[PDB]
Length: 92
Image (cartoon, rainbow, N blue to C red; front, side):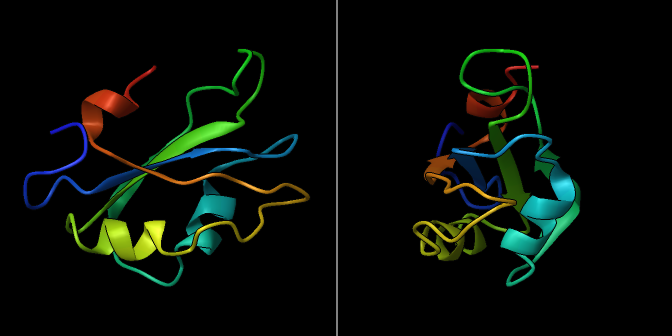
């Protein structure tokens, strides 16, 4: 729950570019194992696009191998990372 229990490993992003989507998160953590639609796209930090998002792995541990990415890129922007679970995540 909200960051930890054992399996509910989510992550949150807050940094995405214009038109950002799942498949840019699906390439971000192409590194790692994720449940079959374990990625969530509510809106950006202002509320008109998708510049924050989230991702549920197969485990809490896989989801912190993912915090271990630190920055990388999506599209043209430059993405924060934080630990998460399904109820930090469900802004939609």
